[PDB]
Amino acid sequence: AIIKEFMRFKVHMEGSVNGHVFEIEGEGEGRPYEGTQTAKLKVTKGGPLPFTWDILSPQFSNAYVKHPADIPDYFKLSFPEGFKWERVMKFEDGGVVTVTQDSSLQDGEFIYKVKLRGTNFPSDGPVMQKKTMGWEALSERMYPEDGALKGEVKPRVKLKDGGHYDAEVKTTYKAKKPVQLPGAYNVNRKLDITSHNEDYTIVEQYERAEGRHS
Image (cartoon, rainbow, N blue to C red; front, side):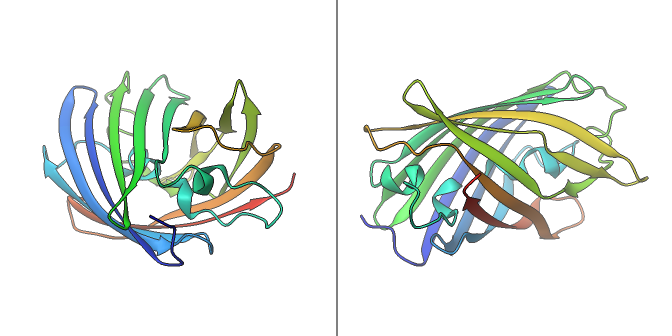
């Protein structure tokens, strides 16, 4: 029931995007104090998915962010009980992804349960047409509000023909028990898909994430 220098996680997602219903199960691992982690995800129901993996990759882990020694680490402090989060991603062309997630620590591993709903993506837009090619580095501002920790960022996905496709992402993180909130700070993140099979039914990804004073 402590957070070791190396930790595994297991994750299950139930999702629907533009009506396409699917599930994903995955196995992750990483170094929670160093802010590095990887995961191997399998689409177990509904594959192959008719849309880009890039809208799913950010839903698969803030226990693995490296925090400065003098900032309360809300995510790590929430364990072993853990924390929940609720996210809305609004994309520039009207698509919307809503996500709810539960994180806990059971028998030495983190257990993540994700529910995702995407709607209103244009049928010929970049998400449904698999035109995106991964996230640029991003900086998420975390700030305390109403006894929870909110994060906000306007991250960008690269397009295969040279553009970018923009989103506004807002997440509320809430520990299951009351834990010390930090003052506002930033989390710098780089999320990469490192391997995948042809139809993206098996995917590996990696994230490096580090908190910094603002």
